[PDB]
Image: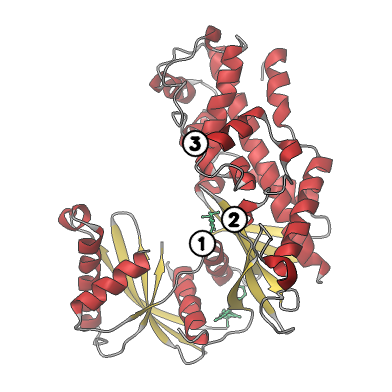
Amino acid sequence: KPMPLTLVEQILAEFQLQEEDLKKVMRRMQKEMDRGLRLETHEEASVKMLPTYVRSTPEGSEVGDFLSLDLGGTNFRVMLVKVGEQWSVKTKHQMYSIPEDAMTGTAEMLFDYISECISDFLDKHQMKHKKLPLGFTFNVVGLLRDAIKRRGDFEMDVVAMVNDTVATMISCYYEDHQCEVGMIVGTGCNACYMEEMQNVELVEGDEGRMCVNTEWGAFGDSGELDEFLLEYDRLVDESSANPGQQLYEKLIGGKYMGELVRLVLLRLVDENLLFHGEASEQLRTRGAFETRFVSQVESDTGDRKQIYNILSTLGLRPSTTDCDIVRRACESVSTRAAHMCSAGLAGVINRMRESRMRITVGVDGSVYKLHPSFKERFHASVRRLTPSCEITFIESESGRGAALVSAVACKKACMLGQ
Ligand SMILES: CS(=O)(=O)N1CCN([C@@H](CC2CCCCC2)C(=O)Nc2nccs2)C(=O)C1
Ligand SMILES: OC[C@H]1O[C@H](O)[C@H](O)[C@@H](O)[C@@H]1O
């Protein structure tokens, strides 16, 4: 690395977060999860800790057979699943490519094509009498119900989807049975984990555990993060659709990460430390610096070409120094996102530890998967904040994890009386 520009470093250093800071954030998250878990304070609690009814014991034994529907980009998978016995997950499936016609009509006309494919599948395997439960993997539930009803020839119960943190936990559990935490760092950020039943005051029972959906994005309503906010965070918060809300997520989520960078670049520019104090009209446009650009700038192999090309797309003609500064502005934001995020997962893992540590954590999300070194910085920060825990991280990815998600969602549904 070259000797950095001092003036720039003083501005980017404002993003730094010390251990003592993250422990502050951690402890504040912890008290907020306590408020969420308890009957008495749950309604005013901003971190809701939603019981998911996904228990540590297999329930809904009378659901052995079901249909799993993995809805993807340009196609979908229909999959028949039979659960037996550890659970014996038997599957057969079919890939269906969505025609361009079906893609480009309306959402209702789309799900009629999906329903049509389901009919063919059931005919192919002689199951059009069986009235199977159907889960979704990746209001489409509503659309499929209406599209099946519209057909009338076969009957089918489309169950409620699980939260994406829960699906991540369940599909990662398939491959590593030590997984008891699900986490998403994409557009938004959330976490779920297996809580002790005695702590889940909203569902009575002492025995076993239940997944709890933290919905921790809402953390910060009472100013729990105020001392750690910066002018740019405040600006993002004011221009957003929901000012004063989702403050924790605003620091971390992919939804705003690009906008934060853009604002940092404008500060630098206005300080005459970047682009000779001259921004483009694109750069002065809200939303122009896409979050994908951040990962791209931080992927640059050292030759400045991915950075140059991105900045050129915004109507800038950057010097080599300008490209270095952008990289460092991107890293500041990323690394701060990773810190803030690690403080949340640390509060969860330390809370789980008190009740008892080798533990696996399932993770998903574009930021965690695709941002060059978010995961690395994130891992190291959590491990630091969680002494006496050994944390294995895995990413969700033959379609049997998805089948296990759909089995749980259907069995949950049976258990709750539909
Ligand atoms: C027999 S098994 O080894 O295949 N197996 C997987 C399923 N589960 C949990 C879900 C898991 C989800 C991940 C964390 C631990 C519970 C489970 O099925 N929970 C349910 N809650 C409501 C309906 S079903 C089990 O208890 C054990
Ligand atoms: O998609 C990740 C997360 O984004 C948002 O925070 C949603 O509120 C939450 O339900 C979801 O788990």
Labels 2 & 1 near each other (Cβ < 8 A) = yes
Q: Are marks 2 and 3 in contact (CB under 8 Å)?
A: no
Characterize the local packing of mark 1: few (<14), some (14-19) or many (20 or more) Cα atoms within 10 angstroms: many
Residue type of the residue flagged with mark 3: Thr
Mark 2 / mark 1, whichever is N-terminal: 1
Quadrant housing residue 56:
bottom right
Instruction: Please tell me whether residue 120 is drawn above or below residue 326 in the rendered image.
Output: below
Residue 24 at x, y = what percent?
A: 81, 46
- Give the SS element for disc 1: helix
Can the viewer see residue 121 in this picture? yes
Judging by the rendered image, the residue that carries numbered circle 3 is 291
Q: Is mark 2 within 8 Å of ligand 2?
A: yes
User: What residue is pinned by disc 2?
Assistant: 190
Mark 1 and ligand 2: say if the CB distance to the nearest ligand atom is below 8 Å.
yes
Instruction: Say the numbered circle drawn on residue 250.
Output: none
Q: Nearer the viewer, residue 25 or 370?
A: 25
Residue 134: which quarter of the image? bottom left
